[PDB]
Amino acid sequence: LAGTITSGWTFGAGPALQIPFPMQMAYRFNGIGVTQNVLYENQKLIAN
Amino acid sequence: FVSGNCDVVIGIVNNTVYDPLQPELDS
Ligand SMILES: *[C@@H]1O[C@H](CO)[C@@H](O[C@@H]2O[C@H](CO)[C@@H](O)[C@H](O)[C@H]2NC(C)=O)[C@H](O)[C@H]1NC(C)=O
Image (cartoon, rainbow over all chains, first blue to last red; front, top):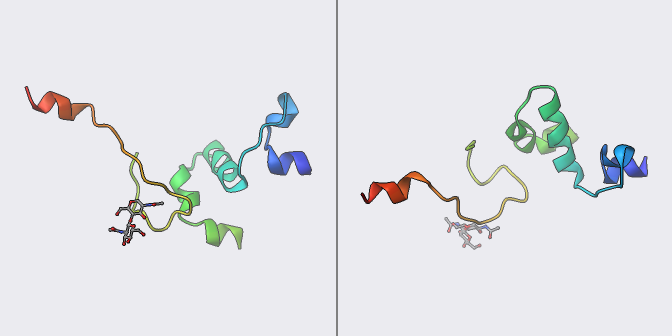
């Protein structure tokens, strides 16, 4: 849990590299075909 | 790419985005 929160997927394929969680969530939105600005404009709505 | 204003995003910062076409406008 600590790795997948502070490092995303990087720790599973090498050294753990820190990255902020709201920014990590933007990466994962890109994986399903959604642009980054969608998350940043609804961060308070998504988090709730 | 551009999307929206500078108010709904938390953590946005000042900076400059360089325009390649502007230097070509002079000539
Ligand atoms: C990015 O630059 C803008 C320039 O408009 C800054 O916005 C102004 O910031 C000052 C300082 O707090 C305010 O008095 C103004 O009301 C703001 N708006 C305008 C239109 O002047 C903004 O603060 C800068 N971003 C950061 C993170 O410093």
